[PDB]
Image 1 (tube, rainbow, N blue to C red):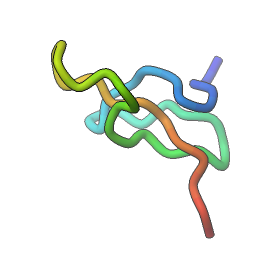
Image 2 (cartoon, rainbow, N blue to C red):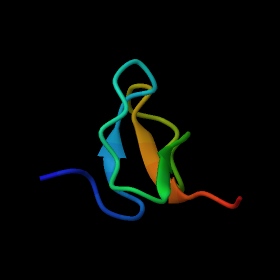
Image 3 (cartoon, rainbow, N blue to C red):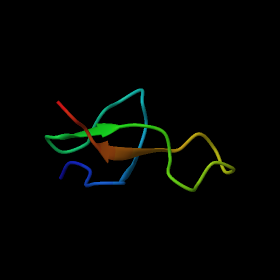
Image 4 (cartoon, helix red, strand yellow):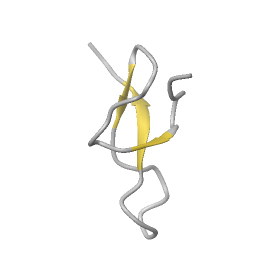
Length: 42
């Protein structure tokens, strides 16, 4: 199943559910470059 809102992912392979987007992390910006999905806006 795709990734949900604020779900861990990578900008190299988008796997977020329709509507969301694999963007940088929220509060986790110290361990690896883990990008968290975010509710896009269009």
